[PDB]
Amino acid sequence: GMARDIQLPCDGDGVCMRCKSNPPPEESLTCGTCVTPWHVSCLSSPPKTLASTLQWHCPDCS
Amino acid sequence: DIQLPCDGDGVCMRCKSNPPPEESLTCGTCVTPWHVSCLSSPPKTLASTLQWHCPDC
Ligand SMILES: [Zn+2]
Ligand SMILES: [Zn+2]
Ligand SMILES: [Zn+2]
Ligand SMILES: [Zn+2]
């Protein structure tokens, strides 16, 4: 997990607000509550189990 | 050898159940849902889970 300070979501156009990159699908995670895309690389605690990755809840919703 | 996906309604064609989101995995190429519980080899990394290719792909 990259972010040691505050974590930022994605653009809505698909750009990570933190690292200024457009994450590929293998690096993208959308929340199960607000459905906001997040760059999984720039998270503080990326999901570590398969179930946590499926029903993933973003840091703003957790 | 007999890996079966989910129907349009959602009932898994290998266990006759409607899996929850914590047990549903949609393929990144043919956008077909699958029941991970009925999968022979579930994904092993985070990248293979985020962009998942179903057995038939
Ligand atoms: Zn990023
Ligand atoms: Zn959320
Ligand atoms: Zn099943
Ligand atoms: Zn497929």
Image (cartoon, coloured by chain):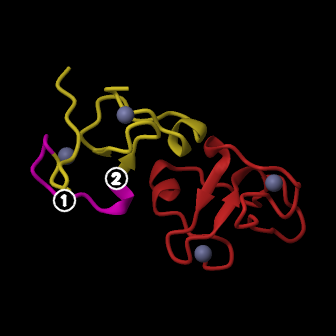
Chain colours: A red, B yellow
Disc 1 sits on a residue from what chain? B
Residue A26 percent coordinates (x, y): 62, 41
Q: Is residue A33 above or below residue B22?
A: below
- Which residue has dot 2 on it? B24
Q: Secondary structure at mark 2?
A: strand
Q: Secondary structure at mark 1?
A: loop
The span picked out in magenta is: B13-24
Q: Residues within 10 Å of mark 2 (few under 14, many from 20)?
A: many
A37 on left or right of B50: right
The amino acid sitting under disc 1 is Asn
B9 on left or right of B34: left
Dot label at residue A52? none
Residue B1 percent coordinates (x, y): 20, 20
Residue A51 percent coordinates (x, y): 44, 55
Q: How many marks?
A: 2
What is the quadrant of residue B45 in the picture?
Answer: top right
Q: Residue furthest front?
A: A13
B35 on left or right of A30: left
The amino acid sitting under disc 2 is Ser
Residue B16 percent coordinates (x, y): 9, 50
B54 on left or right of B4: right
Q: CA distance from mark 1 to mark 2?
A: 9 Å
Residue under the point 72% across and 58% down: A14
- Which residue has dot 1 on it? B18
Residue under the point 38% across and 38% down: B30
Q: Depth check: A39 or A2 in front?
A: A39
